[PDB]
Image 1 (cartoon, one colour):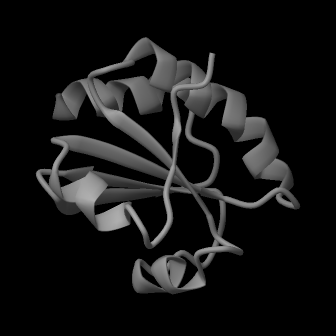
Image 2 (cartoon, helix red, strand yellow):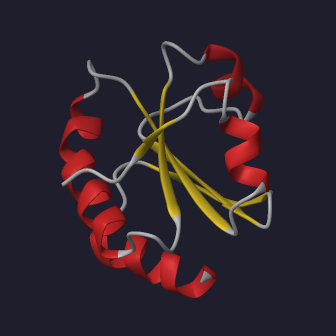
Length: 106
């Protein structure tokens, strides 16, 4: 199942401010590496269902947000803890690295 959450300017801030750990997979359908990373991002999100929010920000529909966090390459996974950015991972993140990062911040 898919427990990831679509983020736009409409809910970006409230989600980050009101959840301890929030990840944001910045992607686009035309991006090959993104397509390969998606199932891994989804798989880890399922493992931590109910414990952290795994958002997805399509960069072509959220240019201002992508720009705000200088997302120049995708995929990029922004990591927010207690409403503030604690990391930004560029490129498809290895599953072990992704799970390790989540565990670390929870």
